[PDB]
């Protein structure tokens, strides 16, 4: 049920954002629909809250032998 | 469970899209977070597909392709594992236990296809001598088909023979030496792309900056962002000096 | 004269989505670069006289970079080709010169940013949200990543074209060589850093096996000594060997095949570790 | 205990000197090591004053003012706390417990006075147009009076009403947000003085050295002494090169 | 001609003890700089013709540096003003140019030395001796600190004047611009270092809350990610914002007020941490 | 009592140092008195001996949020 | 045990070779790994000599001579200790306990001889004014004899009086101050050779590179190999710039 | 004309084995340098006219470097002396100039490599094998070390001569000064590093003795404060003092004697620690 | 006994290497004998195997007060 609700919200927001950008033109319809979708996912993420995963940054291809996690600095 | 023919066609289409996204690396249709959910949707519960994708993504982080170094190819793993879990009735842990051998197999397959496309490149060379642009367009977009079939064919073979455990046995054909040997080789092929770029640059008098960049990355804690900032600063200051430009 | 219509920029932008897709070990991403410039060459060289074939062959040369940050290079070469077709003389080595000069830094700072921080941050957010099993995970990852990819592609093409039409407007002021020089310096620096950071060679031949600290066993190998002298020395020597082989007009395909064979055989023989 | 009027006058004078030294930052009459001993001398035992000053100095180390970032102002704390201890008959620990809220209050007061002196600066601007040097001297030395009263007035109010615990209650008027908010703001106003200097330098082509100095301080263990040595070396070498000066 | 008597150097030295004392948020330490040069302007420009007003306005400009290392700048400007009043032509931007050029490095290495190592070493010695409660504590601190402060002030004025009367003796040899360029380079370097070292912005918005190591709880915030990308990135962006605002002729007082309001409000809203 | 003795010693030493510099001139009377005071405090410090405090060096304005102690390198 | 006269002559020859190798520092005949085995061979069992040499080498690692800083001179220790062990019938641990005082004594002796050879240097100066090359050859090869006797004489005295424990007593003549004072002095004489080279270079405008090399070694983890690479890179780039060479 | 026979290179190589052996505190390794060039001066200056004495005095000057990497300098000076005796004008400061320029870097990277990594690696292998007590220990060390020493000596002489006969073949193209400048830069850098790395001064005067951490006792000395300001500051000041003394034409022998006396006396007085 | 065997092996290998280089000349006799000796010690080292010693690299003159072991970085 929550997944279907999320899909409906995404559809409504994208349609509304496309409608808002109609006077600007076709080049602005995309800039409206994208904004609608982004607002949907942002609102959902804010409702969810924090997350229990390590969130890696500046990692490298550690699958060969390189260091793992943040700048390949972990052997 | 048994699979209806409509679901077979749908899983074929999803596998084709994931295969093409594996080489394009643009829309991330080959990442497990998307491929697993799509397979789950076309096969049954979205719940299990999403969960498998989420669990496998954390492993697949850092499966970058870096300049002729081919990563273990999350697409084939993320598709076949979820087909085996949702249809073959296995535990999520058991399916994710199969992620790594499947990744190695996909790595082998994509390496083979990337060597094959050299024929397409040479055909484009021949089409150049006639000045045929439409031939170039067809040659480029026709080399994606191979990458699509690369994932599509095994993902239909597995789906059609889900009532057997022979896939786990076929996974043991590649014993250990190639599973780990490919990563070891990829620990050195990262060099080749940079070597080709440097060879094409034809700037031998600027080579001191290469060594400077090497040792700086070996004995300091600099980021790559910091190294980019430093490199830009040295470029600007070198141009400010260098009397070749400051001529009266 | 001949000039690029607005409709011929979107055409370059749309075709750049399939930038890879013909990815070889021989000339990586080259056919994609020539494929995404077809709508331009179709306008600047409307006939097959001789300049069309030269223009096509000019772009079927080695070209490897991060797929997303290649739009600026596409725009810059669009501007250069427009000027060269209109008559202003840009040799042939200033086009390929600027292409190769910009290939370095953009691949050196594109990978550690897009395949580096940008993709796994969004992927980790989406994966963590997907552990509970809500659609917000995949949707978040997909939307957030593509809104960055599309933005950088489109606006990179636009900005590269606009800024490249100003580099040629003062031709003779020594701007192309300045830009090539600066790009080469930055690219060499970052590639030198990445060769050390992202490569790994391990030679596990035990040299000494002192046993103390009630069984710490303190094993030292050849790799330990080499890392004490200079970390990443073996990949540096391999880089120089590859450059020497490429000097002798050896096909890169055989170099890559040799690397694969060396890796597999060395791991089988037990002198390449992990 | 009660305080004789002569001691009130003496504590007023000591407070004025400490207040002026707070802004001058020259003789360090505002540091607790000196102010506490002076108050102890004029009030009674030098023993307790010296001990309080010694204990409070170790906290007040690193209460530097750095370019429009105002520190918590040791003067008001070091005066009022010792007045409360020697005259109000409190434990040394209890008095030093009041050092931090008093420091925050003094920080607020000195920020207000430093905004007020802008009127004096503009009056000096007006006096410039008449070429009146004596007016400039009077305007400069007349802006110290405000900084003296800033510490003198509360330090007489407290001394006159020592037979009450209302000061500890008035200390709770500034609840928590401004006590900690001022330090947080001071964590960013350090930037403003450097920004003003850089804006006045009008050297945009030397800005690469700024970024170079930034990242070097973020990923290395260099001192400020070492960074000064490095900066001097780069300045000398830049001048040695740079063909603008090496012209035949 | 007009020259500075010996008695007019002590006058500059004595008045420099009250260097601050009119310290504004608008033009920090500027009125002090004009106040400590009164005995010189009183001699070089004995009349109020027009050059007196120009000389006064020249020194009521922004001038911020460590109070103790400002004697060398006072001496250098004394020499420059002497030469300019005697007739040799020093523009107007070479006086303010050298002042601003020397402001940078002297504030960048003055604070970490005087407010840095020098004051707290003596203060710690005195405080430790004062724990027992002997007068040696405060006396030690007072005497040792003032014997350094007075020495540096007096001999900085003297040395700056003497060395500045040699920079102008070879005017036309390109020495003032060399000195300004070198001082600017060193100052920019040290200020860039100090912006990173001595600033602090903390955004405590929790992004992930993994719990492991039998309860280590491993909280990561937005500040953690930003510090992994580039430590001190937010203060760097704030520096550029302040420079942009000062370009637009915004009064610094409003910038400082805005900073105070932002800090207090952000801490109240709980998105500025500590 | 020790404090009064220290004050008397300081006065005597400053007076003696001023007297020693009389032939040099008023510009040397200060250089003599300062030397006397410095010798007094140095002799007292030598008699006291070591001290039980951390002795910080190259510290910064740690009151905002900066690192504390020796180069702001302590979080 | 007693020693035959032939063994006395042989140990004299081995001591002479070790003494000359101490100053030549070419064939490493003075390292314990070689001297101990040679003494063991000429005296008796090679087994004990090899073992003593192996044990003492691990101590003697890092007994480099660096530009007028004289190390503790492994030759005298490695010879006399094995003479005392093989002939004087002591435990290996007891003999190696004597390695350090013997090293200090040898350090003193070699410092004295290295001050003496200044007379030989001045004699060569005088021979230069006559243009006599054979005199220069004889003067150079005749200054080795002193370094040979430096080790040979005590190594014969010890061998002839092995039936007494007086050597351990004579080892206590140098009490503690010179044993440790010499190493402390050697902690500063490393500077002198570099100072002499820099003084002879007469390049004052390149002195900024000295300070640059100093602080870089104080706050970073760079090797000496890395510092050599960096120095070469800066030399090349300085020559590329520097308009003194890029003149039209 | 006069040229160096092949037999006169081996003669230089053979005599360079006794490169030290007359090692003074006054002119370290100088007589060895003049001794190893005797077979050359015996050919280029067959008579004692005046150039023989000048040639001899030219090489009895201060010359200190790592003994093994001195063959290249020997070869280079062989080439220079050959050209100068044949007539081409090289003066008396380009020979000593190049010698002193090459002394720096070769001693700065020769010691940490030969006395640094090369000798103790082989020595440790041999010593470990000798613990069991087999002849393989000493034999391994001896053979492996001498096969490197002899190779570097012989081929350094050969390569230095061959490369130095090309530096003079384009005399007037500004090559000698380029080489001297580059060698001086590299040498100054490495010597500055080694002065910090390989020196040690310790002043153990206790300043504070805080006691906490249930008895960690946290003693701090003058050396602690100095090391916090700048590690190795005292040896740097001593280097500058030695340079100043050598400027004043003080004999180095007295400097070394003073250093020995200072070390022994300071350790006796207890203010030089260890 | 093993030491005598090692000496005999060294002698045989050096003689054989010298004989192999006879046609090249006296300048190659040395290059043959050296190769023979090197092969002898290398074969012996390979037979012995690993070793129980710390194997130091890039050490300095630690006998004065300098750091000990690998770059003088150990106090
Ligand atoms: O970085 C170089 C670049 O090379 C190829 O185009 C692909 O492997 C990319 O993924 C990679 O980023
Ligand atoms: O450093 C800049 C300088 O600015 C102002 O003048 C005062 O805050 C000083 O304390 C500070 O040192
Ligand atoms: O490094 C300088 C050099 O000086 C002298 O020649 C000897 O002490 C050598 O051992 C040393 O290497």
Image (cartoon, coloured by chain):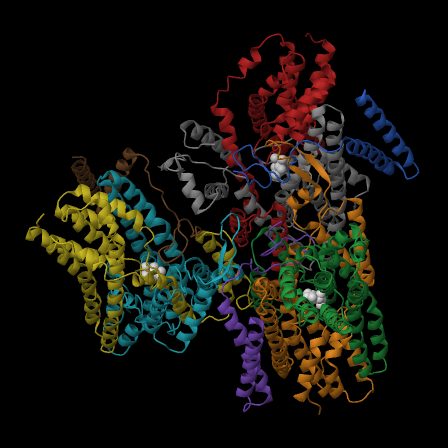
Chain colours: A purple, B green, C orange, D yellow, E cyan, F brown, G red, I blue
Residue D28, given in percent of the width and then of the height, sits at 25, 52
Tell me if B207 is positioned left or right of F54 in this view. right
Compared with C227, B15 (above or below) is below
Residue D226 percent location from the top left of the image: 47, 52
Q: Quadrant of residue C57?
A: bottom right
**Residue farthest right in this picture:** I23
Is E162 positioned to the left or the right of C95 in the image? left
Q: Is residue G55 visible?
A: yes
Q: Is residue F61 left or right of residue A1?
A: left
Q: Residue B231's x, y, as percent?
A: 59, 63
In the displayed structure, B248 sits above or below B210; it is below
For the N terminus of chain C, the quadrant is bottom right
Which image quarter has ligand 2? Answer: bottom left
Q: Residue at x 67, y 24 (%)?
A: G53
Q: How many marks?
A: 0
Q: Left or right: where does residue I52 sit relative to residue B120?
A: left
Q: Depth check: give the residue in front, G167 or G85.
A: G85
Q: E180 above or below D49? A: below
Q: Position of residue C140 (x, y in %)?
A: 58, 70
Q: Of residues D120 and F66, which is closer to you in this image? A: F66
Residue G19, by quadrant, is: top right
- Residue at image position (61%, 21%) is G96
Q: Residue furthest left?
A: D5
Q: Nearer the viewer, residue D61 or E148?
A: D61
Q: Can residue F31 be seen at all in this image of the molecule?
A: no
Res. C218 image quadrant = top right
């Amino acid at each position: 049920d929550p997944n279907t609700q999320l899909l409906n919200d995404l559809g409504n927001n994208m349609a509304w954002g496309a409608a808002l950008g109609a006077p600007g033109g076709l080049g602005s319809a995309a800039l409206g629909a994208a904004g609608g979708a982004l607002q949907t996912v942002g609102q959902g993420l804010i409702d969810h809250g924090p997350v229990n995963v390590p969130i890696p940054v500046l990692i490298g291809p550690s699958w060969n032998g390189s260091g793992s996690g943040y700048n390949s600095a972990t052997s | 469970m048994e699979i209806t023919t409509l679901q077979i066609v749908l899983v074929f289409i999803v596998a084709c899209i994931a295969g093409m996204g594996s080489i394009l690396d643009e829309f991330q249709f080959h990442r497990p977070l998307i491929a697993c959910t799509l397979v789950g949707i076309v096969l049954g519960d979205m719940k299990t597909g999403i969960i498998i994708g989420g669990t496998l993504e954390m492993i697949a982080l850092g499966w970058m392709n870096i300049g002729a170094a081919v990563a273990p190819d999350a697409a084939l793993a993320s598709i076949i594992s979820t087909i085996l879990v949702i249809a073959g009735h296995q535990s999520i842990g058991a399916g994710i236990a199969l992620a790594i051998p499947l990744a190695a197999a996909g790595q082998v397959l994509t390496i083979i296809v990337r060597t094959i496309t050299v024929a397409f490149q040479h055909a484009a060379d021949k089409a150049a001598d006639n000045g045929n642009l439409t031939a170039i367009s067809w040659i480029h977009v026709s080399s994606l088909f191979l990458q699509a079939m690369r994932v599509a064919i095994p993902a239909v073979i597995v789906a059609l023979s889900v009532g057997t455990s022979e896939v786990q046995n076929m996974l043991n054909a590649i014993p250990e030496v190639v599973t780990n040997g490919l990563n070891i080789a990829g620990g050195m092929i990262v060099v080749v792309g940079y070597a080709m770029v440097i060879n094409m640059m034809r700037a031998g008098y600027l080579m001191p900056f290469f060594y400077l960049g090497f040792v700086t990355a070996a004995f300091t804690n600099f980021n790559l962002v910091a190294l980019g900032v430093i490199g830009t600063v040295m470029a600007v200051l070198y141009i400010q000096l260098s009397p070749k430009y400051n001529r009266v | 004269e001949k000039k690029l219509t607005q409709s011929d920029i979107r055409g370059v932008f749309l075709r750049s989505n399939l930038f890879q897709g013909s990815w070889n070990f021989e000339r990586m991403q080259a056919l994609g670069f020539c494929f995404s410039m077809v709508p331009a060459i179709r306008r600047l060289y409307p006939e097959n006289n001789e300049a069309r074939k030269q223009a096509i062959r000019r772009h079927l040369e080695f070209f490897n970079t991060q797929p997303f940050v290649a739009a600026p290079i596409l725009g810059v070469t669009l501007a250069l080709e427009e000027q060269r077709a209109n008559g202003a003389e840009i040799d042939d080595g200033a086009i390929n010169g600027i292409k190769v000069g910009l290939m370095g830094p953009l691949a050196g700072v594109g990978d550690p940013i897009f395949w580096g921080t940008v993709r796994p941050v969004f992927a980790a957010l989406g994966a963590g949200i997907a552990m509970s099993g809500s659609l917000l995970g995949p949707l978040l990852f997909f939307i957030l990543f593509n809104l960055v990819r599309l933005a950088t592609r489109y606006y990179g093409v636009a900005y590269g074209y606009s800024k490249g039409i100003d580099i040629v407007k003062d031709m003779g002021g020594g701007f192309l060589q300045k830009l090539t020089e600066g790009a080469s310096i930055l690219g060499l620096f970052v590639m030198g850093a990445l060769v050390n950071k992202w490569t790994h060679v391990n030679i596990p031949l035990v040299v000494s096996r002192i046993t103390d600290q009630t069984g710490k066993e303190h094993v030292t190998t050849v790799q330990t000594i080499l890392d004490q002298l200079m970390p990443g020395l073996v990949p540096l020597l391999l880089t120089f060997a590859c450059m020497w082989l490429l000097r002798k007009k050896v096909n890169p395909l055989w170099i890559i095949v040799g690397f694969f064979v060396i890796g597999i055989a060395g791991y089988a023989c037990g002198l390449l570790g992990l």
